[PDB]
Image 1 (spheres, rainbow over the protein chains, first blue to last red):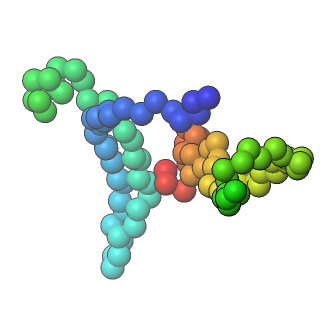
Image 2 (cartoon, rainbow over the protein chains, first blue to last red):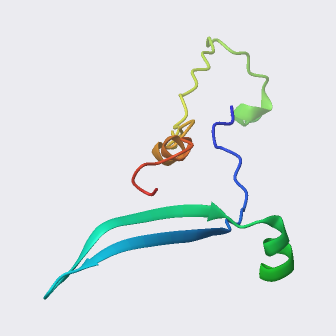
Image 3 (tube, chains in turn blue, orange):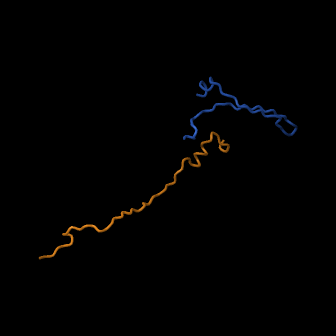
Length: 51
Length: 50
């Protein structure tokens, strides 16, 4: 019996989008929030730009 | 008259035959269905490598 999975190659295209809110003090800076996200790269940007 | 060699006269058998045969030496090799690795790889995801 065959228990090994079927393995193939794939390519992942995405964009890491990070927006940071910073408060600037008298002698220091501080992060009040860091929103990190992953966004898909559209077909019209994979075929026309990346490839 | 003369002399004769022993083999010159027909010989009839007065013995009973027993053909005992020995058991031959054999070797067992390491054999297994699935190695420890194949079982590890059978999983779809592994936490450590991920």
